[PDB]
Amino acid sequence: ATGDERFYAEHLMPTLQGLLDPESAHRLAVRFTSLGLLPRAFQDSDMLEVRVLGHKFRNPVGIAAGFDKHGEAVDGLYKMGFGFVEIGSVTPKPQEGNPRPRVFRLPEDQAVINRYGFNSHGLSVVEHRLRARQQKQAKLTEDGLPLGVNLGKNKTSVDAAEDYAEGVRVLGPLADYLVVNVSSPNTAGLRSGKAELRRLLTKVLQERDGLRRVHRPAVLVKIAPDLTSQDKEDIASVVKELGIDGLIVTNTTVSRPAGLQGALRSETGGLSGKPLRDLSTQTIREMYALTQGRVPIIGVGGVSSGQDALEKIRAGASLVQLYTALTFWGPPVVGKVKRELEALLKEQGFGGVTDAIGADHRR
Ligand SMILES: CCn1c(CO)nn(-c2cc(O[C@@H](C)C(F)(F)F)c(C(=O)Nc3c(F)cccc3Cl)cc2F)c1=O
Ligand SMILES: Cc1cc2nc3c(=O)[nH]c(=O)nc-3n(C[C@H](O)[C@H](O)[C@H](O)COP(=O)(O)O)c2cc1C
Ligand SMILES: O=C(O)c1cc(=O)[nH]c(=O)[nH]1
């Protein structure tokens, strides 16, 4: 462990989180990151490179959606050491989200509960923000640092599929991949038969296919950790039938695992961090098997170490993301996870990340 890792985790982060409300802490982090005011970041080795979704990824550790909802801090996030950045969720029209407070810390559980409710600057604002750096991003992507854009829907929209279609049209041309986020716990009706998922995704794929080739992103579906076995079967079937490019597994949980200690455990919202970790890993495992290992998965939920990352990779993830760990460990967590993952890959006889993807299924 580095000097910075210990100082951030043992002293700086607990101190700052003790002085700030949770949403203020989030907002300041976005500001600092946007300005590049960051501790020095670990040099990515060849072992960490992954080729998937039509792109090179210099390392397999990404920032999950929700940290940079409005695409304000993309360059700072690459500076932090992330191999890829996902922004959003972005809704078609601007919207405020839920009333404050809407983010809650559970430090005794290394967890967070949020009910932001898709607060979003909206597609137009985000479009113009990404256009301002569109060629810089093209070079970053060529250098193995791709960009994902996560699409949401407005609270009052009467046609969910049209909201996602609008997102594809507006931000698709600026993204390496898009995410159809049908799994927020904090918008009424979002997570809801099989035929309607098929309908929605058919429309999204048609819109994507209508973009010019150099502006044509991969399309992924991000799913909840709270799905029934039937839901998971159905999703796998639809994904294969339509040629969806990948899955993001998982969003936050509306469950409250036995054992949570935080005083705020019974707040409404999605739970993230350590209590979500294994529920998410197991969802990756099931989705990989249901798709015969032929559908790339981005694994997310409770990653704070190289071991956590490798467990998701071995379960079937090609790439991982984190968010909640950053709230407790700060920016040095990114180098920590990468260093630990490289060490474990070597210790377990893997030539690189690619060799470990889905390795548990071959035992
Ligand atoms: C879930 C909302 N949330 C929270 C509170 O739960 N904290 N938090 C968060 C909070 C963060 O720091 C808060 C305390 C801040 F900015 F005031 F220092 C950070 C973070 O990485 N900060 C940071 C940075 F951007 C750049 C340099 C140095 C630091 Cl310490 C990253 C985070 F993700 C965050 O996003
Ligand atoms: C405060 C907060 C906001 C989030 N916002 C979004 C979002 O807008 N869209 C989305 O798909 N996921 C969102 N997520 C979920 C994360 O992307 C991720 O799936 C989940 O938090 C699990 O990862 P973690 O345990 O590493 O945080 C959010 C999570 C948190 C904590
Ligand atoms: O904006 C939110 O409330 C939100 C969206 C989402 O997809 N996941 C989450 O945990 N929160």
Image: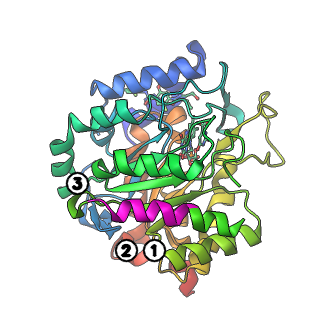
Q: Nearer the viewer, mark 3 or mark 2?
A: 3
> Which secondary structure lies at badge 3?
helix
Residue assigned mark 1: 357
Label located before the other in sequence (1 or 3): 3
Q: Amino acid at mark 1?
A: Ile
* Helix, strand or loop: magenta stretch: helix
Image: 86 above or below 3: below
Q: Distance from label 3 to label 2 (Cα)?
A: 19 Å
Q: SS for tag 1?
A: loop
Distance from label 2 to label 1 (Cα)?
Answer: 5 Å
In the rendered structure, which segment of residues is drawn in magenta? Answer: 200-211
Question: Is residue 41 rendered to the left or right of residue 165?
Answer: left
Q: Quadrant of ligand 2?
A: top right
State which quarter of the image contains the N terminus.
top left
Residue 239 appears at what percent x and percent y?
54, 73
According to the picture, the residue beneath numbered tag 2 turns out to be 354
Decide which of 320, 333 is in the foreground and name it.
320
Mark 2 secondary-structure assignment: helix
Front in this rendered view, residue 41 or 51: 51
Q: Amino acid at mark 3?
A: Thr
- By what rule are the colours in the image chosen? rainbow
Position of 32 relative to 342 (above/below): above
Label at residue 141:
3
Query: Which quadrant of the figure has residue 286?
Result: bottom right
Q: Left or right? Give the position of 296 relative to 185.
A: left
